Length: 278
Ligand SMILES: O=c1ccn([C@@H]2O[C@H](COP(=O)(O)OP(=O)(O)O[C@H]3O[C@H](CO)[C@@H](O)[C@H](O)[C@H]3F)[C@@H](O)[C@H]2O)c(=O)[nH]1
Ligand SMILES: *[C@@H]1O[C@H](CO)[C@@H](O)[C@H](O)[C@H]1NC(C)=O
Ligand SMILES: [Ca+2]
Image 1 (cartoon, rainbow, N blue to C red):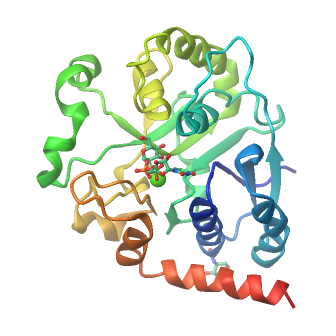
Image 2: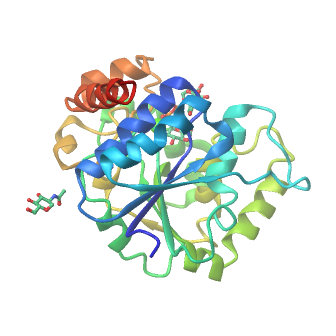
């Protein structure tokens, strides 16, 4: 038909591609529903693209590569990080076929511990997309919660500041509302100021949430140690390995320390790689 769960992600770098395979394995280990992964093709390495049919056949999922060219009229991003962020949030209406009703962005560095079909079924109450809020539970990190003071605290008027690591998009609704055209136009005007949209993929939906509604997802949908308490980890449906501005601990060290099953997925994918080589 089109798959019960449709997930898209973006990865640039061998480290993020290594975590992307782990994310996919974690999704498949926690669901019996049909899954299809969608990749932002141009950022991937030839090795990753060659290995994906092996992952698909081992884990039992479908996949599709999407190559969408940045429109010439639309203000470009010279920083590759920001261009990749642009691909997460600016083209939700054109990356996928009109037959696809819903897609979920899951970060390449995520670890899933839930049946992702529960996010497909989560009620959005008319919102074109749903994001989890940033945690307030780790009190020692309050000084780094930039959204709780200054510009964002005044702008939000008590509304949540949502993390862009995970989000469900009701593509039927998002198209119904022309949210794509509206997000591109707002981004084009806002980005004329190079100081605006510092966290492009995160700031844009948070900025537009008064006119393009966000269904604030349950806090358990996204857990990051930087913002979220140790006590809420047991409830976490998905983990994001977000940067800790206080410790600056490396990415792989965060993965191994925080997530016990991380090495299990990593070793399982490396075992599959050696099996394919024979
Ligand atoms: O595929 C990739 C991704 C990153 N990097 C680079 O890794 C660095 C760290 O960024 P990363 O995306 O991992 O941060 P993270 O804290 O998970 O992001 C959150 O915050 C981000 C917004 O600030 C949000 O997009 C994200 O979902 C949140 F988890 C940074 O220099 C990126 O350019 C890369 O080389 N390749
Ligand atoms: C898939 O179905 C089997 C049926 O025996 C069940 O035991 C298993 O726990 C299910 N897995 C998931 C992730 O739902
Ligand atoms: Ca991340």
